[PDB]
Image (cartoon, rainbow, N blue to C red; front, side, top):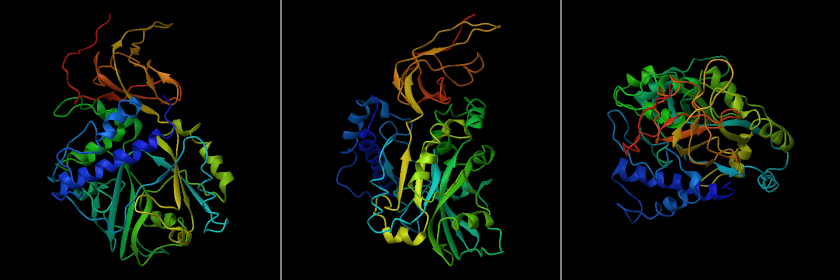
Length: 408
């Protein structure tokens, strides 16, 4: 089941189900007819079962959790739009985009190539250099006031270091991606295990949970990472190309990356796409693909966007590196030095194209302190890209009828 455009039937549905889930729960102000029961949830739920590989811990069709500021979160207001990205097929053309530029750019534009990571969208608001609000995505228009929780730095300053050609804008709204580092996602995943909560599945969900804490003391201890990857509303600034915006974005002391090339033309654009995907695996934190933006600010407003995504950028996206499947039995395997290795056998899954059911656990302590037990539902990363791994179990799936490991 290698999904071709099935992801386009799913990404634009699921994420279009969070919108109303925000509005309904977070606002007491729903926009469409149904509630409690939808409609799209529904044609979504049915789709996820068949084609079954689209399931994720953070899908709104196996989730419900509110809640309301403690602070965990209550509604703010994004200064500008706050929209998604159109998707380049895994795999292929594309160019339909770069030739859509034929239209009204004048094929002499300039493409910005940035790495598109996994994590929670985070818009930040800095008035006169003082960070005021910092909120989640919401429904694009308005989001959850997570300011106190993100204030707990360490990548996101309270202030903007001034002067020497980048005078702090009267108002600056940047927008970026909060994430956990791959290794010390795991170094927390076990550090707890219990003591209140449970182990997280992916760092994609780990980053969400830690952001939305009630006590900001909790989130001041977990690290979290911040990488600013675009502009929202602006007053008394705005560049002329995006980079330009990024020299400024560190002059002021905001976490930028990458790994950003530019990228004179479509040839150098596949030069990076085909470079990552091959090289995508070997980095600090998970990257779903490559996001390509036309450098010159004018051309962007000149091409314009819609209320779904901009016309001036496509998100090129590699095969998904994780999936969710049921850990049927960790049996064993034997080799040549001192130890046998607890190979975890599960039900089949299509991740990174290849269908696999043979994800690994290195050692005794490796196991256990990942919170896994025979019968559990598990998430597996194609982290090599070779031998599959296991990030964590999704505990909210109870059953209670499945238990600890042994073997002597």
